[PDB]
Amino acid sequence: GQMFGNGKGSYFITSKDNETGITGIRVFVGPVGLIKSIQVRYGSSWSEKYGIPGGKAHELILHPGEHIISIYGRYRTFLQHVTLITNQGRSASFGLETGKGFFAAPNLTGQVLEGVYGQFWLYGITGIGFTWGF
């Protein structure tokens, strides 16, 4: 909490479900370079496509024991850039690094990414938020 970017349009939310946490993140990026949609992998199950159809699928598949611990991003009208940095030093960058920047980290140390929410509109994601927990 709360939501990064100029959120506009349809609300979405996904989260952990008495399971393992996030083991993967699928980001869809178009030729225009903005974040169109996301899928989140819980255990072995991919969530539904949250956003606008189109673009090319790019993935961060987490290693055993690996978790996303902070997130840097850029935005304008749409979420332009997202880089997911993990607890093992790895970082996966998606999208064109333009606009107003943000940085999301959990308040308490040991907390990792467990879910993401936000808004998508015309071409893609316009607002993005993150839920952290142990």
Image (spheres, rainbow, N blue to C red):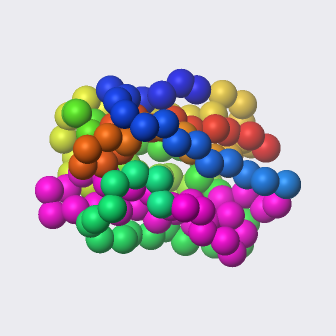
Which residue is painted at 69% across and 75% down in the image? 44
Q: Quadrant of the N terminus?
A: top right
Residue 65: where, in percent of width, then height? 73, 66
- Is 51 situated above or below 74? below
Which residue is painted at 43% across and 37% down in the image? 10
Q: Quadrant of residue 125?
A: top left
22 to the left or right of 18 = left
23 to the left or right of 56 = right
Magenta span has 23? Answer: yes
Residue 126: where, in percent of width, then height? 33, 37
Which residue is painted at 28% across and 65% down in the image? 54
- Is 97 situated above or below 53? above
Q: In which quarter of the image is residue 52?
A: bottom left
- Is 17 situated above or below 104? below
In the image, 16 versus 64, the foreground residue is 16
Which residue is painted at 59% across and 62% down in the image? 47
In the image, 10 versus 26, the foreground residue is 10
Question: In the current view of this chain or complex, which residue is farthest to the left?
Answer: 32
Q: How many marks?
A: 0
Stretch of the chain drawn in magenta? 19-48
Residue 98: where, in percent of width, then height? 19, 41
100 to the left or right of 104 = left
Magenta span has 93? Answer: no
**Residue 80 in view in this figure:** no
**Residue 16 in view in this figure:** yes
Q: In which quarter of the image is the C terminus?
A: top right
Please name the predominant secondary structure of the magenta segment in the image.
Answer: strand
